[PDB]
Image 1 (cartoon, helix red, strand yellow):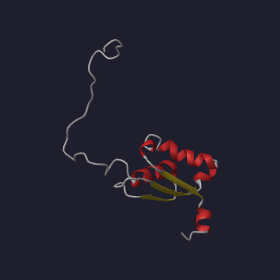
Image 2 (tube, one colour):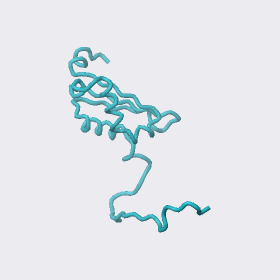
Image 3 (cartoon, helix red, strand yellow):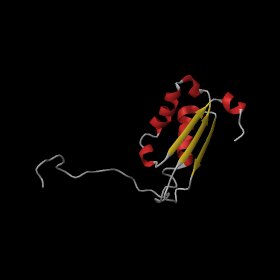
Image 4 (cartoon, helix red, strand yellow):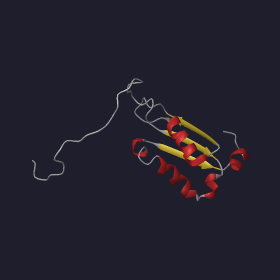
Length: 113
């Protein structure tokens, strides 16, 4: 049907063609280091550790760790919500995400694992 209108002309875009590299699976898109570095610089932490259960599988999960005082200044719930706000668009793509924020004193106090 063509009752409801919205766009008379065709969509357009702009992308220059230059030598460098082609596309792939997700070597650059969606990665542990991507979310790690992003959160680290975005949240500005001291020590961070990211992990993954190998994307090549039925189940996919990502683990992120952050240790600093910047989180202390903000409420407990604000900490977790902060990490979610950053990867808000990426979150939906993550089948399973798990983050944990703590202080440098607590971590250094008891860091067995």
